[PDB]
Every structure is written in C-alpha cells, then in structure tokens.
Image: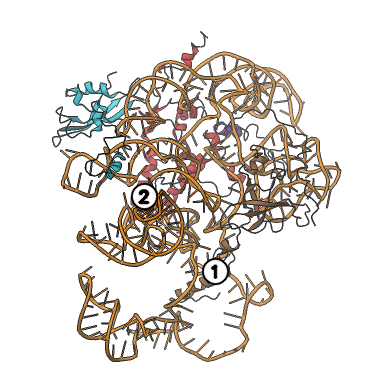
Chain colours: A purple, B brown, C cyan, D red, E orange
Amino acid sequence: VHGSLARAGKVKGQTPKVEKQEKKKKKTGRAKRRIQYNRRFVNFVQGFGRRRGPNANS
Amino acid sequence: MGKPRGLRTARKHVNHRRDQRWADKDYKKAHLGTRWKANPFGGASHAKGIVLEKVGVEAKQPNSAIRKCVRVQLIKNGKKITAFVPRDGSLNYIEENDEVLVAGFGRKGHAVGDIPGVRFKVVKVANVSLLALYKEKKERPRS
Amino acid sequence: TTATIRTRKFMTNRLLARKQMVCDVLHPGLSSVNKTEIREKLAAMYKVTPDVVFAFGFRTNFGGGRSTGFALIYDTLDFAKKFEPKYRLARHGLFEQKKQTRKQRKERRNRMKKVRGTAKAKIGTG
Amino acid sequence: GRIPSVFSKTYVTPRRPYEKARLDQELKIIGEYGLRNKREVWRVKYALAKIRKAARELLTLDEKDEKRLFQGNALLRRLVRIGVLDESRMKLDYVLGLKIEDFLERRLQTQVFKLGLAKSIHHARVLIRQRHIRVRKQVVNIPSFVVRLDSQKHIDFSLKSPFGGGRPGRVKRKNLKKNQG
RNA sequence: UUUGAUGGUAGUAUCUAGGACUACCAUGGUUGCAACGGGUAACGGGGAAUCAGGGUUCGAUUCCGGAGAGGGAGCCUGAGAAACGGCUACCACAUCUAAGGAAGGCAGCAGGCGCGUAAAUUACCCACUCCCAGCUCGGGGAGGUAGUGACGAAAAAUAACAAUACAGGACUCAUAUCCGAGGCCCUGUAAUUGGAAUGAGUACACUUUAAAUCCUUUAACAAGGACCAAUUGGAGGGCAAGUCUGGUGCCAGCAGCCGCGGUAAUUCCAGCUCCAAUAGCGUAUAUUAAAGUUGUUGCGGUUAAAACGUUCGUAGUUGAACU
C-alpha cells in the first residue's frame, strides 16, 4: 500500500534563502532594442569560433 | 487507388467520405456525445469542486516518486476525479475541504506522463490562485 | 486675439430665413475660442446684431491652431426663436424650466392612473 | 454593432517563433530605424504581402483585359504618391521586388533624421512625441506617419513649439526658477 | 390508409384554393437517387474562423425571416392578434386576507436569488436616427448618453542629447598571431556632476454636449532615478538562449513528448546571468492549418492497417468507331 505523504516541502526547509536586494531598473522597450542592437555589433570578432556559443561564459 | 472516376459519381464520393470519416479517431471523438457522458468535465475547459483526500500516486517506472495528487468531487454532476497539484509546497497550502478550481493537463483529455490515469490539474484553491500563492504573492485566508 | 474667422460652404435659405455657414477659426496663441466673443466679431462679418449669430458647434484640430465650426445666421431676432431646436437657446442663456426630473415625472403619470377624473389624492398629502 | 472594430488586422506573429536566421534579420532593422519592438517590423511585412498578392493575381490575366489595368494603376499610384517606389518603375513587376527596408524609411520618424534636425534616430522618437515637429501645417505626434511624395518638401518645425522660444523650455523657465529656491 | 392516407365527386367551412372539413365512389400515394423512424449539445439564411488551391469548423449574437412570452388550451374587440407589459380556465408555482375573498407572470430596461468554468449601473435625457397620436409643440429605459469593462481592433509612457571618470575595436603610425603616440568613424559602466527637452499627472478658463464627463485645445505647476521604479514565461533537445554558484540526494520535485534527479544535477530548488515576445504574455478546452494522417484536386491495400473463398447478378457507375 501507500506509506506516507509528509515528505512534501523538503527543499523549502533546506535552501539557505539568499536574495537579490538590488538590480537596477533597465532600459525598456523603446531603448531595450538599441541596447541589444549594439550587443550584436559592439566588437563583432569576425571569426570562426571553433564550435562555440553566443552568450555563454566561455 | 480505387475511386470511381466517372462523371456522375458525386453520389458515391460524398457517401464514402461520410462512411469513412467514422474510422478517424479525431473526427469520431467529437461526434459521439461523450463530452458529457464520459468527460467528467462538462464538455468544457475548467471545473470547480470540493476535495476529499490527499493521496500519493506511485509514478510509472523508470521514474519512481510518490506524486501527491488530490481526489476531488466536482459539483457539476457529482463525479469524483483525481487531480494533480504542481510546484512543491502545494499541500501544506491545501488544508482539506477547501473549494478548488480544476483544469486540464494538456494532451486533450487523456493522461500525460509518469502519472498513470491522472488527467486534471488544480488551478485555484479557496479563490486565491494556487500558482500565485506558491510564489507567495497571494495568501490563503486563515478563515 | 482677432480669431481670424474665415467662412466657407456659405449658402442662404429663406425657407427658414437662414444663412448656412461653416467657419474656419484659427487658434494662434492661447487656447480654443469662447463662443460669446465670436458673436460680436461675426457681427463684424455682416453686422447681424450679435444676439442672432448662434455660432454653436466647434472642434479644434490636432496640435493646436485651428477650428472649423458651424454658424447658422438667422435674419430676425424671432425667426431665431421660431424654428430653433430649443436647447440651442439653452446655451445662449434664456431658458431653464420645469424640473421633472424625467424619473419623478414618469412615475407621476403612473401614480395618477389609479384616480378617477377628480384626482382627489393629489391635494391631501403630496 | 456593426461590426464596429472592422479589423483588417496588422501585427502578424511569425510562423516559426524562435529560429535565428530570420530573428536577426529583423533585429538590426530596429537598429537602422530606432523602432519600438517587433510588431512594427512585421506590420509593414503584413502591409507588403497584401499588395504583392494583389500584384500577383493581377499578373495572372492578360493585357489588354480591363480587369488587370484598372486595379493595376490604382496600386502603383498609391505607392508613388507616398513615393517608396518612383516613376521609373511603373509596372506590376517592380512592385514585387520591393522589400520592406525602403518602406520603413518613408516613415516620418526617419524623414526627420534624413534632414539634419534629429541628431539621432533614437532622439527622433522623442522629438516627434514631444509635440516638436510639423508636416506642412500639421503637428504630428506619431513616428509611423508615412509621408507622401510631395509632402516631403514641407516637414519643418512648428513654431507652436517651444523652439524657438514660445514658453521656451519650459525647463528654460525652470532654468531661472531653481535660483530663488 | 380503422380514426384522410392518394385521387374523383358534390358539398360545407374560410378572406380564398385545397381531404381543410363531410358524404359517396376509386385504390391509390412515398421507397436503395435512402422513403419511414431515431438522434441533434438544430432556430434557417446573410455571414464568421482558418488555408496556395481544394476545404473544414462555427453561426445564442445588433440585418432579413420564423418562433415564443411559467406550462397548454380558448377567445373578445379590432383592417390587422389565437395578442399574454388583453382576457378566460386548467396545471405548476407563488401573493394578500379581518378566512368572506382579491390579484400575479422581467425570454422589455435596470436589479436580486439560483445554477454555474462563464457575463456590467436598481445612472441620464428624447438633442440624434426614426416610429406613433386629434398629430410643427405630446410620448417613446425604441434611441442617444455617462458609470463597469485586458472579449476583441487601432495609434503608442517607460527616456533623449552630450561631457570627463574608467574603458573597446578601428583609423594614422612606431610596428605586424609581440608593442607606443593622436586611445578611437567606438561604446559601455558610472546614486561621477552639470545641462536640454518634455506628456504622465495637475489646474484657471475654454471647447464639448440635451446637460455633462473624457479626448483634442489649455494660463499657472510638474524628472535625476533612490524614482513617474514592466512584467509574463523559459535557459538538455525539439526551440533562441550560463557545461555559473550554493542547496538537496530515484528524495523533493521538474518535463506537452524525448527525457531529468540515486551527496560534481548543463533539466530540480535558489542566488548571478541570459534569451524570446512585450503592456503584455503564460495555462486549460474547442477548432482550423500543420495533415501528401480522410486524399475531388491528392493516400494506401504482395510483406507495414487493407482485394470479399468463389463466380453470377439487379439497382448504380461507365460505356468502340461513324454524320
């Protein structure tokens, strides 16, 4: 038969609850599409990146 | 293959596709009246109900976890179904015999994944929108 | 101010003794016009005794600076009070009568249905 | 009643939603014309496809049959009165070569930049929507004003505007209001 | 088709044809080209949703037509009604009553209960469009008009221009997968700081309207982000997007499907970031496309689902040449 159910919420009494506290209301719709426009063209390495990714760490 | 290619065979053609549409599983599902006789939802998107018991469904293997479902009797025609609740938390936020709003799960009626048989999903409980109280933007009243 | 009232679509009719006219009013510096000072300077258009002007309809164009509006010039002072949809003299202020109030009135004519001829009930309580 | 919102609905969402080789064709279109978002982009793509199918199904008939010509000349005239296509290309084939990146530069939000007054295409949305622009007499507060061909001669300032000086800032009034406080 | 069904015949009845009704004869009439019966979550049509075409689904819903006012039946007056904001009765519900009796039908406009996944004000006026009357003038919750309103459509706030601060490639040139100077046709991060704009609000007055409000027009007020502070979803693949950091350990859970998770988790839970569409977007049900998986255009049937065991054979469908 069924044993029990009381193991629910085991993660929520376990995580150490770190937060954000900040981060800066950003450029919205009219000016968001020109921030991300130059991020398609700021440096633009012009290279075959040897099977790489666009917005990874490295 | 087959079909009569004569000039006056419009009688046979519209007879045939009427005859042979009743083999299609998608046509004949919507043309038999069982969205009210077999569907415990009243041919509709949502339903409301009152719960009975909070139970653990054993998931289908390879996966193995008790799945924490709720067996509810909806008030529309008194049928007793079992719904799934998402987003862990979600049962210390129920506190049995609160009025719940229930929806579908997604595969157009029948069951979905590792949970065998369970086809419906709880949306609101005691008016306060379970997906919003999970992120604690709404609080369930202590009344 | 000077308002530059320039008139177009001009036509007169003595079927009801009127001058049908739409006027183009410019809004050069401050705001939209007020109707009562268009009167005496549209009584500088043909000198038609400014209380018979009745230039009552207007809308300012987008951006600010213009207004095309209607002005019907009656000839005499009481042909102005002859045809005249009567709420236009409610603007050119001479009339305010009979509070009803269109709900109390429409239950007057239903309450007095249960009397017979004399209406002896309207004199006692009220 | 009636049909009130008689749709002719623009703003067509794309068929396949994520694939990059069409997602970044339209992203620098927002760069070269400093638009709001992607719905202004495929709006004219919605506008382009209807005149194409007009010019497509007109091309299925023969000249001279009067079905083709009579809706034909009304198509190209409305283009050249706007002036995205012009007077050397006045038959039903050159309209099919018209893509969108000349339609999105007949808009008045780019006409104000092609004459030396905007100093940025992202300043040009702000100057239009601050009631500081005029076409031919009229103060216009939208970026997507498609201009007509002979209307291009008359986009100026309004002198209704606080340039040059009518209630001149009124942060210019606030320039000498910060001193007494 | 006894108890009108198909016809004849004479009638009655009606405004009139007619089995509409009567009386007498005749035995007809419909049917595999689907009659009859049943179902319908059926008011019909204009039309609506969706596709390259061919199409499928829907249409309670503002326009025309039918239909009905709790359920049935009857009927008066009227040119016109089998009228129910007319009457009469029965049936079901309710109402008042001093117990004798008297009246009621919101599927009109508002409003309340109820059922429900599921739907707003017990507001204002006939100025509009027209209708009606004895009829320039009266009346018209027809109609217009505000209040609710993210059903749905449209135009578009959430910054912009420069400076140095720290900084990138590139342009000239010492030089060349090393390296300086003008760092620069660059852009970011700067509670550095200082400037230019402004509608969002706000407020005189105005226009507005039947009287209003809102927008438009507006004299005075109004931006330095700490704020006027954009969020909804996802970051394994399908599917554009951290092999980030802590937590947990086939657990909690996630996942449309494939799949993840068993003290290194690219999939959970969180932090730090990122990507999509953006005043939006997610979920559920239905429906269309996708679907060459309903196939007229256009499928398949040796083995994947599928040529009747066999041949006759009527209905049906197709049928040589010749003027």
> x, y (%) of residue C27?
32, 23
Which residue, given by chain and number where applicable, does mark 2 sit on?
D72
Q: How many marks?
A: 2
Label 1 marks which chain's residue? B
Give the spatial CA distance, label 2 vs label 1: 45 Å
Q: Residue at x 33, y 51 (%)?
A: D70
Nearer the observer, C16 or D22: C16
Nearer the observer, D28 or A12: A12
Mark 2 nearby-residue class (10 Å; few <14, some 14–19, many ≥20): some
Q: Is residue D18 above or below residue E50?
A: above
Q: Is residue E320 above or below residue E220?
A: below
> x, y (%) of residue D128?
45, 28
Label 2 marks which chain's residue? D
Can residue D99 be seen by looking at this rendering?
no
Nearer the observer, C107 or C117: C117
Give the secondary structure at mark 1: helix
Which residue, given by chain and number where applicable, does mark 1 sit on?
B21
